[PDB]
Amino acid sequence: HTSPLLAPVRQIHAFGDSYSDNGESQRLTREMLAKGIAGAQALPGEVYWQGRWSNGPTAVEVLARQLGAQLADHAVGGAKSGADNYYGWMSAYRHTGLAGQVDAYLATLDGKPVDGQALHFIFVSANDFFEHEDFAGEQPLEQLAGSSVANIRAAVQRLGEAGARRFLVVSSTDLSVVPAVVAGNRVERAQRYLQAVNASLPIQLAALRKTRGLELSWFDHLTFSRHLRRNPARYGLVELDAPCQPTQPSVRPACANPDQYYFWDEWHPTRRVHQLAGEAMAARYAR
Ligand SMILES: [Cl-]
């Protein structure tokens, strides 16, 4: 039986990674190139739509449209759950991880308190895993998962202390079906990581609900994707595994029918899956 709808939302503050970014990695990396920062590259790049790491709006942009809310999207492609980014060269210019996004959001408020009616949307952790795998991190995956969860809990705590009262926390996605993960033969590594994050994060959300009357909503992105992938024709999808827009080892021409594809590139969903995700997220809220 469904629960009561949550209250209407008119402002979203989003924090997170390339599954949310609607233009911040592009703005920041253009700034970094203009200032000659060492190692800087223009992100996301020329096979991506309007600064999104996809071919269309991300899930949180669709959530905002569905709810009739304005969106301040702080998320930055590459962001980890702590201070920094999968792209190490950014750290000398700006701390763009979740913790850095929170720092900057609170610093840009003038000592002014947070809007207690705004929805604080948090969606991060993938790059903690991608960085670990791609650069041979030595931490066991269960400890990495613990670190990601502690970082997320810390961000909620810091935002709540500053005055936030409404949150939407997104689970780990199904990293085990990400094309780069599959091509790297890292599926069971991804399963162990994502299951540890997703088991532990709801327990931390229970603890945080004990003060400030925090509304801490959980979006289980794994449940969402498993349902879509088990019933793809219902949603107009056909190709669940191959990227529409290959980039590795080099860029190839995009597929003709991108709304029938789950993945845009080797890491990111297409606009069609972001739409379905945003609609699923929005279903918990009144208009
Ligand atoms: Cl562009």
Image: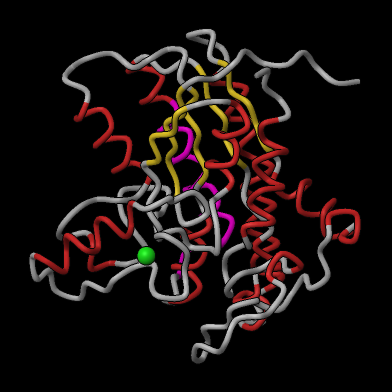
- Eyeballing the image, is 12 above or below 115? below
Residue 260: x and y in percent read 76, 67
Q: Quadrant of residue 141?
A: bottom right
Does the magenta portion include 217? Answer: no
Q: Quadrant of the N terminus?
A: top right
- Characterize the magenta stretch by its predominant secondary structure: helix
Image side of residue 185 versus residue 44, left or right? right
Image side of residue 103 versus residue 73, left or right? left
Q: Name the residue rendered at 49%, 91% in the picture.
A: 250
Q: Quadrant of the C terminus?
A: top right
Image side of residue 130 versus residue 255, left or right? left
Q: Quadrant of residue 104?
A: top left
For the residue pair 28 and 86, the one nearer the viewer reads as: 28
Q: Name the residue rendered at 73%, 16% in the picture.
A: 5
Residue 209: x and y in percent read 57, 16
* Ligand 1 positioned in quadrant: bottom left
Residue farthest toward the left in the current orientation of the protein: 35
Does the magenta portion include 145? Answer: yes
Residue 165: x and y in percent read 47, 15
Which scheme is used to colour this image of the protein?
secondary structure
- Eyeballing the image, is 179 above or below 202? below
Image side of residue 149 versus residue 242, left or right? left
- The magenta region covers 138-156
Q: Name the residue rendered at 43%, 51% in the picture.
A: 21
For the residue pair 170 and 119, the one nearer the viewer reads as: 119
Residue 133: x and y in percent read 51, 73
Residue farthest toward the front in the current orientation of the protein: 256
Q: Name the residue rendered at 45%, 70% in the picture.
A: 138
For the residue pair 192 and 162, the one nearer the viewer reads as: 162
